[PDB]
Every structure is written in C-alpha cells, then in structure tokens.
Image (cartoon, grey):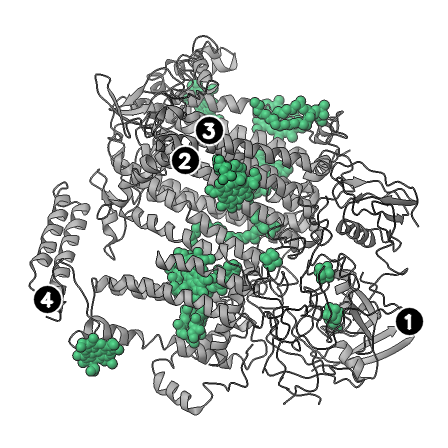
Amino acid sequence: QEAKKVRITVDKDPVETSFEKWAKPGHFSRTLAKGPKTTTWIWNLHADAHDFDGHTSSLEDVSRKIFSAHFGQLSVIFLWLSGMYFHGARFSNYVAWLSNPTAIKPSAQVVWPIVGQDILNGDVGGGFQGVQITSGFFQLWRASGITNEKQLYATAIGGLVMSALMLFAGWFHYHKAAPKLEWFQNVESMMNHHLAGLLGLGCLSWAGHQIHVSLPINKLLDAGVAPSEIPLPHEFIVNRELMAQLYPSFSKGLTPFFTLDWNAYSDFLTFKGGLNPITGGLWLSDTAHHHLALAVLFIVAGHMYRTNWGIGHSMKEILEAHKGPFTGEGHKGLYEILTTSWHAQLAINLAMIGSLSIIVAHHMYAMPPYPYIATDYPTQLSLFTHHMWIGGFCVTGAAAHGAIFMVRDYSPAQNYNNLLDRMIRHRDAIISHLNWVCIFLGFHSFGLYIHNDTMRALGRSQDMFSDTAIQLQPIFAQWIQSIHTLAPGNTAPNALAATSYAFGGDIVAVNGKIAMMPIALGTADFMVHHIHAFTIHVTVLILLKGVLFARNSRLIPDKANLGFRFPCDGPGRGGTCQVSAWDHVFLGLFWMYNSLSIVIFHFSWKMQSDVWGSVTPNGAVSHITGGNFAQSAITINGWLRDFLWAQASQVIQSYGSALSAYGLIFLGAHFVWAFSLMFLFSGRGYWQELIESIVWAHNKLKLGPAIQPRALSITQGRAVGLAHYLVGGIGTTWAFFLARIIAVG
Amino acid sequence: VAGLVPCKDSKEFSRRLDLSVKKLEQRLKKYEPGTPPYLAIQKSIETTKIRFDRYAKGGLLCGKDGLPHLITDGRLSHATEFIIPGLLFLYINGWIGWVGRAYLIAIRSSDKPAEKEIILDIPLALGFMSSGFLWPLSAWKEFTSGELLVDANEVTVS
Amino acid sequence: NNFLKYLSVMPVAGTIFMIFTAGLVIEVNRFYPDALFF
Amino acid sequence: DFLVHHAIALGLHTTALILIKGALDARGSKLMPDKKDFGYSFPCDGPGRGGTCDISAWDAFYLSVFWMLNTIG
Amino acid sequence: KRGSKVRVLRKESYWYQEIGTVATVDTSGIRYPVVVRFEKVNYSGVNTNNFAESELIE
Amino acid sequence: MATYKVRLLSEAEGIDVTIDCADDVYILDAAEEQGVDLPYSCRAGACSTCAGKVSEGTIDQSDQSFLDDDQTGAGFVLTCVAYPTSDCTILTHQEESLY
Amino acid sequence: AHSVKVYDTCIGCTQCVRACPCDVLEMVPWDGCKAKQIASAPRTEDCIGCKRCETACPTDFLSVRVYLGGETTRSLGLAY
Amino acid sequence: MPSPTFGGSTGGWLRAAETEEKYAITWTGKKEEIFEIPTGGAAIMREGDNLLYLARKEQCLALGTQLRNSFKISDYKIYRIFPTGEVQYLHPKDGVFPEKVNEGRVGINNVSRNIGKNPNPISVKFTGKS
Ligand code: CLA
Ligand code: CLA
Ligand code: CLA
Ligand code: CLA
Ligand code: CLA
Ligand SMILES: CC1=C(C/C=C(\C)CCC[C@H](C)CCC[C@H](C)CCCC(C)C)C(=O)c2ccccc2C1=O
Ligand code: SF4
Ligand code: SF4
Ligand code: SF4
Ligand code: FES
C-alpha cells in the first residue's frame, strides 16, 4: 500500500549556491572536466549541456535537474510574454486600431532610424509609423477585451514579476529544497492535478474571464461604441445590473445554475456556431460556453486515478489487464518503463504536443476564433504556418527520444514478451510494408504530377488527370462536407448555424473582404492530399526504422554498445555510413521540411484562390489569384509557374518599400541554405587536412594555439548542415509568405 | 575626367536627388504636421539632401547612370575613396594580428595553457592589448630579430 | 576572485567586448552617416 | 562587371584550392601518412582519430565539380 | 638519455620536429626503447608515444 | 612537488612495497624509481594492462581515456595518469579485474 | 579477403583483440617490449574490415593497419 | 563436438535461406537469466548447456561478448555449420581466449618494419603487394 506514501520527500539544502563550479566549465562529465586539449571540447561543451544521463547514474539528481530547468524555461515564456504586452503599450497603434480594425494594419515595432533603416516603418495608419506585424496579438487583445493602453502596460509588468517568481522557483528547487525520486514517481497523483487543477481551473477561471469581461466588452465593441466610452471591466463585476442590460439572465443571478435551471443561461452560453458577421470571427458566447464545458469534465476526468484516499483507477492495473491473444503479455511492464526514464515520457509527450499544434493550425483557419482576424489574411497565414512547423519539429523529437530510450534505459530482462519487445521481434514486417506503401504512394501521387505534366507538354490535354480529363474526384472528402451542412437541424439539432463555413453553406464577408467561403474540394486535391499522405509515410519510414533498429540490426548486432549518437561502425560490411539512430532523426528531419513545405504551399495557393478576395454588394466574388487551382495546380510546372514564380513577384519587386526587409531575408535564406551543403556534402577528413595546411601557417609564425584546432566531428558536421538547411529552407518560405500577403492583401 | 564625368555637375545624379525626395514627400502628405510620424519623415528628408550635398563637395566621379563611383587606380586625388580607409583598416587590423600573437607567447609559458585560452587572463590580455598602436616598427624589428619565423627543420610538417 | 573570473570566459568576455565593438560602429554612424570617403 | 569577375576569381582560386590540395595530399599527411599505400580511390580511413570521411584524393576531386559548376555557372 | 626535451626525426607521427619530453629509457633490446611524452595532443587523443633511439637530436 | 606514500601489493607474485611519490609524478614512475616492475603498455590512460585497484586512498585518475564511468565506480585506476593526492594503499595486477 | 597486417611498433596493448568483434586478431608472444607479446592476424579471410582495431590503437600511427582489398559474402556482412 | 540442444525463445527476425554458412554458439549457463538475442528480442536461458543458431558471425561474437560482460561466464563455444554439415570450431581456436597469450605461436601477417617504411606504389607495378 501507499497509504501515506504519496507524501513529499524533500532534501533540505542539497547544493550550495556558489561560484567555483560556475566558472570552471565542462563540470558535468569526466571527459570534459580536464580542459580543452582539443577543439572537440568546445563543441562537446554545448552538446553535453542538456545530456543529463551522461552526467550521473543517480536518477534522483537527474530528476532534480529536470524540474528546476522547467522553471528556467517557464521564466523565458513570461519574459517573452512581457515583451509582447509591453510593445503593445509603448510601441504600438493598438489603441488607434480598435476604433477601425478593418483597414488599419497592425504594428508593434518602431525601428530606430540609424543606417537609413527607417524605411521599414511603413504607413500603417492610425497616425502611426512602424513595422507591419503578424503574430496576431491585436485580435487576441480584442478577444480578451483589453481596450486602453494602460492594461497592456500593467500586464507586462505583471508578467515580469511572474517571471521573477518563476525564475526564483527553480533556484529554490535545486539549492534549498529538492524533491526525491519518491515524489517524482507519484504519477497517479500528477495526472490528477494536471487534468483537474491545471486544465479544468485553467478553463473554469478563464470561463470567468470570458463571461464577466470579454463578453460585455465584445457586445459593446461591435455595436459601435468607442473604446473610451465603454465601461470598465471592474464595472461589469460590482454592478450586476449593468450586465443585466446586455444579457437579462444576470437579473436572476446564480439560482438557475445552483438549482439546475441551466436553460435560463442560454442567452449568453449558446450553441450558435459558425461565424459572427459583425466582428469577423467566432461567436464569443460559444467560446465562453466551450471553456466551462471542458472545465466541468476535465475536473471530472481529474479524479480518475488512484490517490491517497483509497479510490481511483490504478495505472499499474489497467495497463496489466490489457493482455490479448496476438499481443502476448499485453502491457505488463510499461508502467515501470514510464516512471523511470524521462526519455520514454518525452517520446510520448512530444508526439502529442507536436500533433496537437497541427490540430491548432487546422482548427484556426476554417474557424477563426478571434474578432477581426478573418479579414487579416497575413495573420491567418502566419498563425497557420508557425503552428505547422512546431508540430513538424516536435514530432521528429518523439522519435529522437523514442530511440534514445532504447539504447539507454531499455532493459530486456524487464521486458520479456511484453508489447515493446514483440515489435523488436518482428521489426522486418513493420518497415517493409511501410517500405512498400511509400513506393506505392509516391508512384500514385508524384507520378500523376509527372503524368499531367507530360500530357500538357505532349499537347494532348485530354489524357491528364483534371476536371475536363480522366477525373480523380475525391468522393470521400466531398461527402463529409455534405454531412456537416446537415449538422445544423438534423444531426446535431440544437446547433443553429454550421460547425464551420469551410464545408459549405454560405459565404461570410466582413466590410467587403471575405471572412470565409466554402472550400470546394476538386480533383486537384485528390492528388495533393496523396502527396501529403506520401511524404508523411516517408517520415515515419525513416523514424520508425530509427526506433526499431536502435538496439541492433543485421548490419550491426551490438549497435547499442557504441551508443546512441555515433558516426558508424567502419566502412566494412560495404560501408556503415549514417547507421546510428541519430542519423535516422537527421534523415527524418529533412523529409519533414520536404513534407511541411508542401502543406503550407497547399495552404498558400488554395486559400489565395478559392476563399480570399473581394465581394461586390451585388454578390460578385473576385478572388486573389482568380481560382487557378482548378487547372494549374495539377502539374509540377504549374506549381512552378503559377505559384512559385508568380506569387514571388510581390517579394522581389519590393525594394524601396516597407516590405524591403523581407527581400533581404528572402536572399538571406537562399544563402544559408547554400551554406548548408558545404557542411552536408563534404566529409571531415578533407577539412582536417585542409586545417593541417593552416596550422603550418601559424606554427611558422609562433601563432599556433595551445589547444588543438580540429575539424568538426561527423555527427557534429551533419548537425550543422542540418540546422543551416532548416534555417534556409524555412526562412525563405517565411520571407516569401509574409512579403506576398501583406502586399496583395 | 579619368574616364567618365564628375557627379558634381551631373543631370542624372541630380535627377536622383529629384525623384527620391519627390517620392519621400508623397509619404509626407498623408500625415499632419506636429505628429511624431511627421517629424520622422521630415528629418529623413534632410538626411537625404545633405547626403546629396556630401557627395557633391566630396568630388566623386560618376555619370551616365546617376550613381556614385570609385577609382582604385592608385590615384592620390582619389585617395579618400579607398586608400586612407584602407590605411586605417590595415593599421588596426595589425593590432589584432599582433596582440593575438603577443598574447599567444606568454600564455604558452604557463602551467595549464589549454584552459587559459578560453578562461582569459584579463590583466594579461589587456596587459598585451594597448601595445598595439605601435605594432609595425616592432613587428619589423621582430622580423629581423629572427624569432618571428621558426626554422623549417623545426615545424610541424607531413 | 571567481565572479570577475567568470567574466573572463571567452564568450562572455567576448560579448561585453562585442557589445562595445558593435556599438562603436553604430554610434559613429549616428553622428556621421552616409560616408563613402574620409 | 568589376565585382562579378571577382566572383569568377573566387571560383578560379577555390577550384584550384581543392585540387592543389587534391594533388599534393594524395601521398601523405598527418591524418594519414600512408595514403599512397591505399590508392587514389578508397572510401575512408574509418571513424578513428577523429573520423576520416572524404580523405582520399578522389574525394578531394569530388568537391571541385560542385565548385567547377559553381564557377562556370 | 634521461630527463630533458628530445626532438624527433622520424616522420609518419603527429609530433614531427617537435619538442618532446623523454621518460624511462628501456634496456632490453626492444626496437623502440624510449616512451617519450608530448604536449599538444594528437588526433587519437593520446599525448604519449614510443619510438626508437635513432631519432633523438636533443 | 609534495610527498605521498603508496603501499603497493601484488599477492599473485607476493610483493608488498611502500613507494614515495609527488603530485606531478605518476604512480608507476615512482614504482620504477624504487625498482618495482609493473605491467604497462604506453603510459597514456588508454590501455587495460596497467590497472590497479584503490583499496584505500584518493587518486586523481582523471587523465585516462580507456575506462568508462561505471568501470571506475568500483575503483579501477590506471597507474600511468594517476596523480596520487593522498596517502594510499593500492592493490595492483588488476588488468583482468576490469573486464 | 582483406589484409590486416600488423607492423613492428606493436606494443602488445591488448585491446585490439578486445575491440575486434570477429576474433581475427589474436595475441602471440614475441620477443620485444615489457609486454612480450605481439598482435597477430590469422583470420584475414574471416574479417569484415570494420576497422575496430584502429580506433583503439595508441601507437605513433596504427600498429594494426587494416587496408581493405578483396571481399566475399562474409566480409560484406549479409544475412542472406 | 556439436550436439542436439535448444535455446528457448520466440523470434521473427532471424536467418533467411542461408546455405553457405551457419553455426551454433553453445554454452553452459547458471541461472534462468533474460538476455537480448543480437538480432533482437529476449530469451529465457536454461541453466544447462544451450545453443543458438544465427546467420552470420557478427551476431555470433556479439552474443558471446554480451554473455561475457553481463552474468559473466567464460565458457561460450562457437562452431560453424556448413550446408553439407561440417563443423569448424571457429572462435577460441585452441581452448582459450585470444586476449590471453598463447603458447602456440603462428605469427602471420606480421611485417617487420615501421609503417613509414613501405615502398612506393611505382615499385609495385602490375603485381600485388602493399
Ligand atoms: C493543481 C496544482 C498544480 C498545478 C497548477 C501545476 C502546474 C504545473 N506543473 Mg505541476 N504538480 C502538481 C500540481 C500542480 N502542477 C503536483 C501535485 C505534482 C506532484 C505529483 C506536480 C508535479 C510536477 C512536475 C514533476 C512537473 C510539474 C510541471 C508543471 C507545469 C507544467 C507547465 C504547463 O502546463 O504550463 C502551464 C503553466 C502555467 C499555468 C503557469 C502558472 C503556474 C502557477 C504559478 C501555478 C503553480 C501552482 C503550484 C502547484 C503552486 C505551488 C505551491 C507553492 C506556492 C508553495 C505547470 C506550471 C512541470 C514543470 O514545468 O515544472 C515546473 C514538471 O516538470 N508539476
Ligand atoms: C521537449 C523538447 C526537447 C527537449 C527537452 C530535448 C532534450 C534533449 N535532446 Mg532533443 N530534440 C527535440 C526536442 C527536445 N529535446 C526535438 C523536437 C528534436 C527534433 C528536431 C530533437 C532532436 C534531438 C537530437 C537529434 C538529439 C537530441 C538531444 C537531446 C539531449 C541534449 C540536448 C542538448 O544538450 O542540446 C543543447 C542545445 C543546443 C545544441 C541548441 C542548438 C540550437 C539549434 C541549432 C537551433 C537554433 C536555431 C535558432 C532557434 C533559429 C536560427 C538562429 C539564427 C542564428 C540563424 C536532451 C535530452 C541529443 C542527445 O545527445 O540526446 C541525449 C541528440 O543527439 N535531441
Ligand atoms: C527529388 C528528389 C528525390 C527523389 C525523386 C527521391 C525518390 C525517393 N526517395 Mg528520396 N531523398 C532525397 C531526394 C529524392 N528521393 C533527398 C534529398 C534525401 C535526403 C534527405 C532523400 C532521402 C530519402 C530517404 C531517407 C528515403 C527516401 C525514399 C525515397 C523513395 C520514395 C518512394 C517513391 O516515391 O518512389 C517512387 C519513385 C519516384 C516517385 C521517382 C519518380 C519516378 C517516376 C514517377 C516514374 C519513373 C520514370 C520512368 C517511367 C521509369 C522507367 C524508365 C526508366 C527505366 C528509364 C524514392 C525512390 C524512401 C525509400 O527509399 O523507401 C521508399 C526513404 O525512406 N528518400
Ligand atoms: C553558398 C554556399 C557556400 C558558401 C558561402 C561557401 C563558403 C566557403 N567555402 Mg564552400 N562549398 C559549398 C557551398 C558554399 N561554400 C558547397 C556546396 C561545396 C561542395 C561540398 C563546398 C565546398 C567547399 C570546399 C571544398 C572548399 C570550400 C571553401 C569555402 C570558403 C571559401 C573562402 C571564402 O569565400 O571566404 C569567405 C567566406 C565565406 C563567403 C563564407 C560565408 C561568410 C559569411 C558571409 C560571413 C561570416 C558570417 C557572419 C559572421 C554572419 C553572422 C552569423 C550569425 C549567426 C551571428 C568559404 C568558407 C574553401 C575553403 O574553405 O578554403 C579556405 C574550400 O577548400 N567550400
Ligand atoms: C590571434 C589571432 C589570429 C592571427 C594573428 C591569425 C593570423 C593569420 N591567419 Mg588566422 N584564424 C584565427 C586567428 C588568427 N589568425 C582564428 C580564430 C581562426 C578561426 C576562425 C582562424 C582561421 C584562419 C584560416 C582559415 C586562415 C587563417 C589565415 C591566417 C593568415 C593570413 C591572415 C588572414 O587572412 O587572417 C584570416 C583571419 C580570419 C579568417 C578571421 C580572423 C579570426 C579571428 C576573428 C581573429 C582572432 C581574434 C582574437 C579574439 C584575438 C585575441 C586577442 C585578444 C582578445 C587577447 C595569418 C597568419 C589564412 C592562412 O593560412 O594564410 C596564410 C587562412 O586560410 N586563419
Ligand atoms: C568547412 C567545414 C568544416 C570546418 C569548419 C570549422 C573549422 C568551423 C570554423 C568556424 C568556427 C565556428 C569559428 C569559431 C570562432 C569563435 C566564434 C571565436 C571568434 C572570435 C569572436 C567572434 C568572439 C568542418 O569541420 C566540417 C566537418 C564535417 C563536415 C563538413 C565540414 C565543413 O564543411
Ligand atoms: S566517417 Fe563517414 S566514411 Fe569514414 S567511416 Fe565513419 S562514416 Fe564511413
Ligand atoms: S593495437 Fe597497436 S598497440 Fe595495441 S596491440 Fe595491436 S598494435 Fe600493439
Ligand atoms: S579489422 Fe574490423 S574487425 Fe578486424 S579488428 Fe580492425 S576493426 Fe575489428
Ligand atoms: S600503459 Fe598504455 S595506457 Fe597507461
């Protein structure tokens, strides 16, 4: 039993906060504590900075290094959030933006006029000059209902003091009072408070902020009241009857909620759905209804697990009883896996918080949450693409530490015939059927794009795959849009408007600019979604080969004895170049950019052709690129001509304007991208012999360093060609996306 | 002269004065006088005019495209365009080239020289710093003393 | 010792020198902009 | 046209740089003093002594066709 | 020769024409009877070496 | 150059000596300076033949490259990078004892 | 069909036989240094050429040269 | 020298059709330990003598090296099974590990010079030498 063994077990004053280990670096390992005889020591100082399992075998002081370092991470978020709210105060036009947010551009950066760099401060209206900016805090602060300039100045000084508490908390949990491993292995209580007292109260108190503040502000903003003439947020609390003049349910009080007459609160907790045509966004009373819906059953889902007081589903027992006929012993052993190694826990946490942020990017463009974000097509493009790439980067880290756990913390004595062992036993049939389907998909997705490109080149346009050709109609994806337009009335009978206007229904347009149009999925989207199904399958072809062949293979039967990150096992067996599980992540990261650039290119052409544009008061709709995705999207030359060559004209004809900083980054990240391939195509032994000429040029002149100037190591040399490629593969997509949509829209 | 025409009297160079301030005054007529974005443009108007009076009195040599050009045929009349920028450049390039060599001899006669290259001896690094405005009369003395160059039978070689 | 000798590590002794030697070039471009010569 | 010949003369000296390294370090070095006993076109010397990818004079040739096409491009 | 610094004469090592530091000269008829140490460590991370008595110049 | 004492003992051959060393001198260099033969390969910290076991004492063994973290957790010190910073008693001939 | 001949420096630092995962290196007692042993290579037909001796080899430069020549299905490491 | 015994496991990643070389790493244990098969998975390790058929000799040595470090036993023997059925007794080669110094000295592939003392490849012209 653990009838008093969920308690706190805290060491008092473990580490003296001193200065002598603070200035003698490399102090976390035996191989780095004896000075830099070589220049591998400087690059090993940064690579072993967060490799805590190579520092101590004691898991108690490993897990105290994790918990204090999260406070250092969370203090960086509050310092960065203070930089957003302070630049809304002293360096912004947001207080001028609220009087007319339909045509005044957002601005949160005034550049110092120094080198003649003042031309980037553009005429963004409001009597204000500055850089046009696209992170979308301005529609967030209208969604929360910050009206005046003082509340942004108070939050950033309220956020800086929240960082100074959060930075102090990591100091207290490594130098005065540190928990033990008994406290960290109480995971049946950690999922209780995180479900209930983090996300439930994180919703329920936020539902308090939305009902009492953001709903009376955004009911008075869209009526046409100036933001100087709206009553204050502490007048919608101490005066109940002022809320009663907006929603008449507040004249009654708390008695419908306590006595369960909850249909009396329908006037401000509704199920409208769809959009709000006055302010250009989601119905805020739906969002105020959505948060306490999640709150009242996250706290219900909080009390699921076993705690101090007897009741609760034990996490060791629900896992153990899931055995089956095919699955051998079931999950017998996985609970001791996840409460010992953090890398096993990080490999599941990164796939979730990665692929929840891809859900964020898809559940934001077609359901615009924030008011007056619907007309601002630059903010929809930047908030899509940034939530893609974080969900693209954090998903390859799930197979980073999925492979780091296998070589370090996977003991096969504790894993006889359980569920993790059985896929190491049949790891040929996992990869080979994944190896077949990528050749099946890439012939059937990219091979059609060649086949439409040849038939246009060979003259015979009646032999490609188009609407006026051999049609490949996406009949499954065209069907579910016809279901969600019957989701009002029929299938969900209390939903008045649609669940989203992307599936169908009606257009919504705000001040002429189109808020949301129905997306008509045609035969050019059967192929580009199959592109997306292909290149996702290749990324899990490299990465699941990295996890299942992390221990051993038929090339190397003792791969885990060399470590996780090693270059090779010699040029024998024909050559073992890039054989580690590190290089599978290094190979798998490249196809992610070869995946996610296509997803944001499918975004930036379809939404520039079918939904965004202009609406005449008769009802005539004229889009930006004229709806050229019906024909020109089906060929690789059409992706080159009508999208890559054509939409980059706003980037490169933008010198002398305020978008001219983006043209420098557009040439900046062609350069860093073709700085990568020096680090990527070449080897090490060339440059080490090339450095060998230069050490002669210094030892002739008494100029040689006492440290040894070496070439970069091979995993280090593959890593610097990796990070350069993903700066120069993303930064020019960044500088072409932002420069196009600010210019044309 | 020396090829093309001077830009002290050049119609295309004076046209680049004309349409640039005509472009920049078009931004001025959408604001109101007294605002801080109005003063940010009008101060940026005069720093383009005085720039166009800097190159006129400087005697730059260009024409046929309205730009300024530079001459690096060793011309002493054109010494202000490349030579005395390079003579200040090569002056205290040769600080860092010499005091890095001066730092790397006294650090070799130490107990642990490997740690001392990234853990600085700041009273020695500044102690070998300010003897760097007077480098090349001492570096030439170092070249003819003999120990600036070690002998070829004691170097590292393949 | 050992805190001013923490301000002798080559990045941080570089960076407070790099804060200095960047800003030497910035503030001479404050008072003398637009210089092709002298 | 002043500046762009220096883009050619960058690529003229750099494609010379890989290959005068590629000629004169086919025999030996400090990283491999017995490169002559292995031949012109061998893969590597392994991961030992720091790692030795692209050590051969064939792989010292191999980098210049990138720089040759960069230069004549 | 005990003690002091001894320069090398053989090629194919990392330390060629370097300073050297001799230690414990061997007397058994072994081909390489000095186990001379060095600073300025090699590619293998080994600051020591043994070679023969034909490469001293001191 | 301080003074330190190391009591070496090899029970397979049966030799127990007390040698004197300094902070810069290695342990087997002091064993060769008192006339005691000891196994070694190249005096680098990068072999297995020169392994001794620290029975009592404190040894700066940190300049080696052969032995890993756990294999030195039992107290196996190569005698050729060892700076004896204490007065110790060391069991030697432990070259098979590490592996 | 490689050729993994061992040179004359050859101090008997018995870890190349330890680092060989194919048992193609084997110590032979031989008149020489205080270790009194040399590294011999009998199984050159059985080797893979994965160069695991050379990474653990603290001589001047490489007591066990490896230099890769011929090959077979054993040396190429195929399980089929 | 071989004998019919077992190993005790389950697996699905092993030798294919292979008939040029196989073997049997045979050893005596001491307990029901759980060990990683070098092609993957786990096994149960019956306390008497037991054997493993695997494909190629890297898997055979890396199971013999893994058995020496964890649950230390210096008694593993390695054969080689031909397609015709002949045995070889490959690995210890005469009753002992090769890191121990033998008394039977063959001494082959032992050049008697330094590695710089090797001729130029012009001197080995149209023939086979270093
Ligand atoms: C209901 C109580 C509660 C709350 C709110 C949290 C909240 C958090 N925990 Mg936590 N935890 C709890 C109970 C709670 N825990 C218990 C009972 C245990 C033991 C079983 C743990 C064990 C635990 C571990 C081991 C770790 C966390 C981590 C985290 C952070 C996750 C980051 C995040 O989601 O961003 C959301 C961020 C915020 C909402 C920021 C605001 C946070 C404010 C200050 C509330 C903090 C409440 C705190 C529990 C009060 C402590 C009392 C103290 C004043 C004396 C977050 C701050 C992780 C972390 O980041 O470490 C710091 C981590 O590694 N917790
Ligand atoms: C939850 C987030 C998270 C956390 C905590 C870790 C934690 C860890 N990872 Mg990991 N990883 C993650 C996400 C995460 N990773 C993701 C998402 C990926 C896929 C991209 C990887 C891929 C990965 C690999 C491949 C490896 C690790 C390793 C490690 C370990 C040491 C890391 C270290 O010292 O780096 C120190 C910090 C740095 C080196 C910072 C470098 C900064 C990079 C280059 C980005 C900079 C770009 C910049 C932001 C923008 C441009 C700048 C401009 C100048 C152009 C540690 C356990 C390594 C290890 O040894 O594991 C045990 C290892 O081999 N991880
Ligand atoms: C544009 C360049 C390019 C191309 C076409 C490929 C092609 C491929 N890569 Mg690949 N790759 C590339 C760059 C490229 N790579 C780069 C830069 C890297 C480094 C990051 C990698 C790293 C990499 C990995 C790590 C993996 C692949 C994989 C694959 C295969 C995916 C399956 C597929 O679509 O096959 C179908 C083939 C095509 C679509 C090619 C076009 C063929 C057309 C459609 C028809 C054929 C023409 C003609 C009719 C043939 C007959 C005539 C001919 C005989 C003369 C495929 C062979 C995966 C793999 O090998 O397993 C599947 C895998 O895991 N790649
Ligand atoms: C556009 C991509 C690119 C770039 C810039 C370079 C750059 C260089 N290569 Mg290279 N290379 C490339 C691609 C590239 N390569 C490819 C694809 C290959 C084929 C594999 C090679 C193969 C190759 C070989 C084989 C050789 C070179 C050599 C060189 C150097 C030439 C000397 C020179 O120009 O000095 C000037 C340096 C540069 C132009 C590099 C960029 C410097 C930047 C712009 C300034 C410094 C950065 C600055 C501080 C910015 C701030 C950064 C911020 C994070 C703080 C230089 C480092 C030669 C060499 O190293 O000789 C000395 C050589 O032998 N390269
Ligand atoms: C003490 C500083 C110092 C000195 C005097 C030299 C001197 C020289 N280097 Mg050199 N170099 C240095 C540092 C230094 N280097 C560093 C740190 C690197 C690594 C980035 C290199 C990389 C390097 C290469 C790759 C090459 C040279 C070459 C040369 C020679 C020609 C001059 C040239 O173009 O410079 C080259 C200068 C650079 C590429 C950049 C300068 C590097 C830094 C910024 C200077 C160090 C500043 C340091 C903080 C000073 C400390 C003083 C104080 C703070 C205590 C010349 C002998 C070339 C050669 O062999 O010609 C014969 C050549 O190809 N160097
Ligand atoms: C060029 C190249 C090198 C050589 C690159 C080197 C040696 C890096 C040199 C640049 C470093 C980063 C300079 C660091 C200097 C410090 C910043 C100090 C400078 C002084 C001030 C800025 C403080 C490799 O080592 C390599 C390895 C593997 C594959 C490809 C390659 C490769 O292409
Ligand atoms: S370095 Fe590159 S080439 Fe040389 S061995 Fe390791 S992988 Fe093979
Ligand atoms: S590796 Fe070098 S040193 Fe160790 S034994 Fe073989 S030859 Fe002698
Ligand atoms: S050749 Fe390959 S196998 Fe034979 S020893 Fe050297 S590394 Fe080990
Ligand atoms: S004797 Fe070879 S490493 Fe110490």
Disc 1: which residue: F11
Instruction: Determine the chain carrying the residue at label 1.
Output: F
Q: Which of A371 and A730 is in front in this view?
A: A730
Marks 4 and 1: CB-CB under 8 Å? no
Residue ID at (63%, 90%)? E57
Task: Locate the C terminus of chain A by quadrant.
Answer: top left
| Residue type marked 1 | Glu
Tags 3 and 2 touching, CB below 8 Å: no
Residue closer to the observer: A329 or H48: H48
Kindly identify which chain the residue marked by label 4 belongs to. B
- The Cα atoms of the two marked residues, 4 and 2, are separated by 52 Å
Q: In this view, does A422 lie above or below A576?
A: above
Label 3 is placed on what type of residue? His
The answer to whether any part of residue A353 appears in the image is yes
Q: Nearer the viewer, residue B98 or A443?
A: A443
Marks 3/1: CA distance?
A: 75 Å
Q: How far separated are the C-alphas under marks 3 and 4?
A: 62 Å
Asked which secondary structure carries label 2, the reply is helix
Left or right: G22 as drawn, with respect to A210: right
Name the residue carrying label 2. Answer: A600
